[PDB]
Length: 209
Ligand SMILES: C#CCCCn1c(Cc2cc(OC)c(OC)c(OC)c2Cl)nc2c(N)ncnc21
Image (cartoon, rainbow, N blue to C red; front, side, top):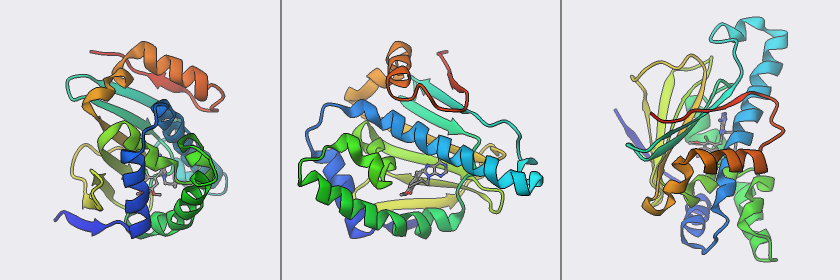
């Protein structure tokens, strides 16, 4: 069964602001997502110093960027800690409620969208370039899940029966039609070099086809 949930009003409100505001510097979505991956990798690494069996689901700690022009997707893959079902439906949204308010406040004081990450809600910058975001994730403690949202005030969560991923997260960006520059290898390298050059995990940029 696919379950459908409503975003908290404040999140819905943040998402519409990100979709509707005129803001050309969309490219920062990628450093926000890579940074989320790096944090998630830090987390599993740390946890495994006191419980080595936490890496039975995979020793390798890395990030893959995978463009597919045929599907028009850019996928950010990591072997980090993953997210549980409670993370997906409740935990992360509760936390996010306070960062959203603060971010929205800051924007009315002349902050700009690029600073979203300082408020712990940078995930939602995905909606600068994606019409739909699909997140497949597996945490050691839980089953594999798929989250998706096209905004519009709702998201879904289902158990994922696709290919098992071991441990980690895939964020699949279904790009807006005018945002296909982020499928281009030279454009991606440029952004990773500009914004994400000092990440402490290998970042492999996959090419097509
Ligand atoms: C906020 C924040 C960071 C924690 C959640 N998270 C994120 C960002 C994130 C935040 C969310 O809510 C605030 C969220 O749900 C709406 C979310 O999921 C669909 C993601 Cl991927 N990316 C990763 C990742 N690659 N690996 C592990 N946890 C992640």
